[PDB]
Image (cartoon, coloured by chain):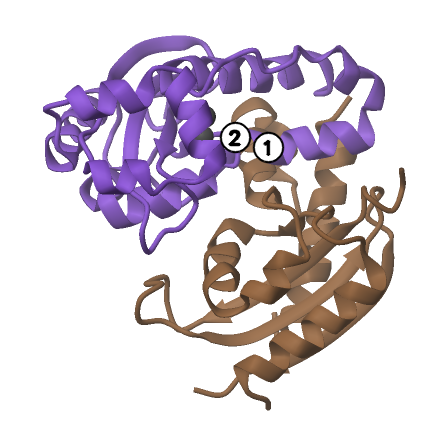
Chain colours: A brown, B purple
Amino acid sequence: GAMAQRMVWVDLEMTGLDIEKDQIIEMACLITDSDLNILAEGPNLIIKQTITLQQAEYEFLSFVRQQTPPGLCPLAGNSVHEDKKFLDKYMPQFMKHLHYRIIDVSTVKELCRRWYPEEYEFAPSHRALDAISESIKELQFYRNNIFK
Amino acid sequence: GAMAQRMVWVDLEMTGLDIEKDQIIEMACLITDSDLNILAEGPNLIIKQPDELLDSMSDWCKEHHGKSGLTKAVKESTITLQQAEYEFLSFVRQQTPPGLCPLAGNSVHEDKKFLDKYMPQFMKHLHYRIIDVSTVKELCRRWYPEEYEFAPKKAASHRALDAISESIKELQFYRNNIFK
Ligand SMILES: [Mg+2]
Ligand SMILES: [Zn+2]
């Protein structure tokens, strides 16, 4: 039904893309429904190398436990495959609550660029919570402009 | 332009989902153009991994890889990871310009985790971005439930070459039915 089709939107900032040496600097989270309407906003936490990593994982895991069913909803965001690699390593209990599938907005951007080049030319941050809001609007823009 | 807009399709079969322990046992590669037209079939290799790792696999892994004939073909293989990487890197360099084409497939971020660790030179030839057919699958389920039911059931056994052809068939299905 509608609940199993909710999305767990995230945005993360790291020191780099090397999973062995880089760390999660900032993170934000929010839930939407299947039609991208924001149901709830999670926290916007800056992590030390302000709060520690293990506490952010508790904060974020609490937030999604009260908003989504266990192991059902996918992680959503722009280049969220880069974010999932770091969440699978540094927040494994948070990732245990989600599905293995992602709703990656940059996959949709790559298809828009190839298949709908005019729409792509006119396709549309200080916090990680603002970067999520921008990705939702980008995903909503593709739904209206390139999907049937 | 057109050569930079080609897609690098990949399917892996591993001994499990543990990046710290598990290894790659099968790999297939295929190239399509921007519009998902079939351009070229790449290698389809079964990579040799120890008997300890195969006997200590998950109950799902032992049963699915056993029935498919993969665990038997892995024990008989003479292909190392280094040998397969070289064959896969060679093939994509003949097909695509460096660092411009994405990796494509179903939840291909999991295949990228294993390729980033075990075939880093093959990943250096591809762009940063991926084409995850499972993102489009999730949006189809949600926004196009009728079309989603009409999509064909994944009929392939976990053989890299058969799996990669079905991910292409699945993205083509979405392009044909849920895109403008
Ligand atoms: Mg696979
Ligand atoms: Zn498979």
Relative vertical location of residue A42 with respect to residue B60 in this rendering, above or below: below
From the viewer's perspective, is A72 left or right of B13? right
| Amino acid type, callout 2 | Asn
- Residue B11 in sight in this render: yes
Q: Callout 2: helix, strand or loop?
A: loop
Q: Give the residue pinned by disc 1.
A: B134
- Image location (x, y in percent) of residue B60: 49, 33
B97, above or below A82, in the image = above
Q: Residue at x 80, y 33 (%)?
A: B142
Q: Nearer the viewer, residue A34 or B77?
A: B77
Residue B12 at x, y = what percent?
Answer: 36, 30
Query: Is there a contact, CB below 8 Å, between mark 1 and mark 2?
Result: yes
Residue that label 2 marks? B106
Left or right, B3 with reference to A120: left
Residue A130: percent from left, percent from top: 69, 68
Q: Which chain hosts label 1?
A: B
**Under 8 Å from ligand 1: the CB of mark 2?**
yes
Residue in view at x 31 percent, y 37 percent: B55
At 61% from the left and 29% from the top, the residue drawn is: A118
Crowdedness near tag 1: few (<14), some (14–19) or many (≥20) residues, C-alpha within 10 Å: many
First in residue order: circle 1 vs circle 2: 2
3D distance between C-alphas at marks 1 and 2? 5 Å
* In the depicted structure, whether residue A14 falls above or below residue B124: below
The image quadrant where one finds the N terminus of chain A is top right
Amino acid marked by disc 1: Ser
The residue sitting at 50% across, 59% down in the picture is: A88
**Pointer 2 indicates a residue of which chain?**
B
